[PDB]
Amino acid sequence: MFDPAEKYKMDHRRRGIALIFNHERFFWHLTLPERRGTCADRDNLTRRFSDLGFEVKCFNDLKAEELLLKIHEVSTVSHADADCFVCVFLSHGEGNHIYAYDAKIEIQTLTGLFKGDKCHSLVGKPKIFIIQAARGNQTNITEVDAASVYTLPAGADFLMCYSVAEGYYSHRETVNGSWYIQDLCEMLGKYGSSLEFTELLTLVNRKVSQRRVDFCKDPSAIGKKQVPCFASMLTKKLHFFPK
Amino acid sequence: FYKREMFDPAEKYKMDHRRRGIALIFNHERFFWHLTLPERRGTCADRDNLTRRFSDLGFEVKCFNDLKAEELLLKIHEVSTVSHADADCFVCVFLSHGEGNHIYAYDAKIEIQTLTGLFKGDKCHSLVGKPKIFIIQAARGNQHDVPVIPTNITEVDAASVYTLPAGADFLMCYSVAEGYYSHRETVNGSWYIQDLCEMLGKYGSSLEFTELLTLVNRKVSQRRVDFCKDPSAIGKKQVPCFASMLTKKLHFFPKS
Ligand SMILES: Cc1cccnc1NCc1ccccc1O
Figure 1 (cartoon, rainbow over the protein chains, first blue to last red):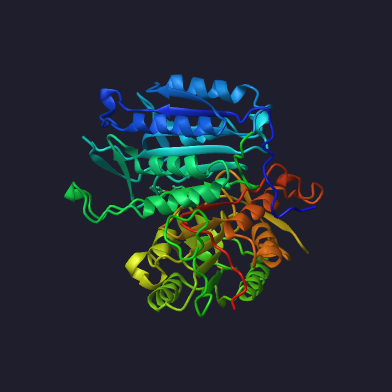
Figure 2 (cartoon, helix red, strand yellow):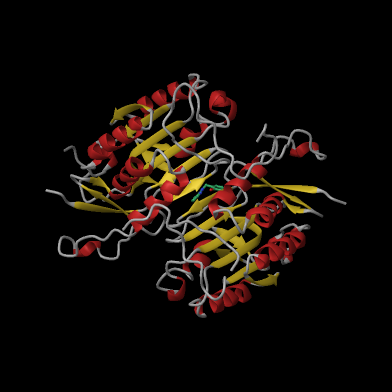
């Protein structure tokens, strides 16, 4: 019958793939600023997800064609033996788009590759996108970017996680990494293997939104609060218990 | 514990105020002819269903039928400016058609950000740190009716309203996501609202609210239309979603 506490079956041979697309620099014609600190984010995410059982694959500064090719490749292999799929974007963005090295890519194109009829072996399984992307400004310094990327939904069993909501600001420390990724990774490390994942994301919401912007080193950044959000199309409770 | 102090993985919104709070329902069944929008038969079932479920959870429910945009704005501004100091939370429901960042009132559209903006920070100080929950059943009205002055059937409308976020401690709940379709039975009401209300009744007073919304996601996305009744509705799946800016666990336990 109908089960109020039903969980995604996470008893497969493998947890699954976690893809990370990391962008630090951009083709000069795009006139986008470098993203110092993003490599800290990449490393942090890599440890957390690998500790959760994911097979983590990182890609640095791919051109759009290369990026599309790689994600299409992954969408077309069998995930039959996997619990789930994770995809992380660390870049600048605008509207429905995230930037690769040389051009933008639509988020809907990326998520569309993992919808039911495109990726049968992921049907009914969690498909999690984590997006750290905002408006590029055209030792440890905090850079502040206006929210620009739409907090888009996707298909059933997708979970779309965004560093920042409309009207707020994304922060990135050049040594320590992004506020959002730091707090996400801290929560993953402590609670990732026990807490329901949207419960955990809610903790991240609290952590990030409570960071004070009262007295920034850069006075221009005062009052520029960060509020993350996630859009859930999940249909069951999601845990990452040790396999 | 003996007394608490640190970062708590299981922190819950404090729901021990004198009152649960206000639940606003804006119910729109018909529209000014110049808008060229179809009527929304079944929405009154949705309104009544929601009224019962939220009142059982302790909310003070106020319904408004077919308000003009100016009246709507006035009313919600009125609620945003009173003191919610004695309240746990705030709920606002829109039952209408919509487009992009807009929801239709009787005579004009209103931007969702205009509505949520009224309840941010010191615009509504007494709701700061409290759940502010918007539930939006709004999609694209099928316009095969004229620009002139004018049984249980399932109407199927394309998703049209952006699944917009808002401020901290907002929870924005949407009947349908981009690329899918919202369904409304002309007697029984909307798929989304029916399933939301059933889950509220069975689990609302114990389940964490986003967990409950996740149940609604499952219920709705698994619904099929009777192939013989409307073949055109084949492949028009409904996938709801919610955008959470919540910072704590939200329960509606019976108030003492
Ligand atoms: C068009 C849209 C679709 C879904 C969600 N939000 C959308 N627009 C609002 C918006 C603007 C800037 C940054 C984030 C953000 O969410």
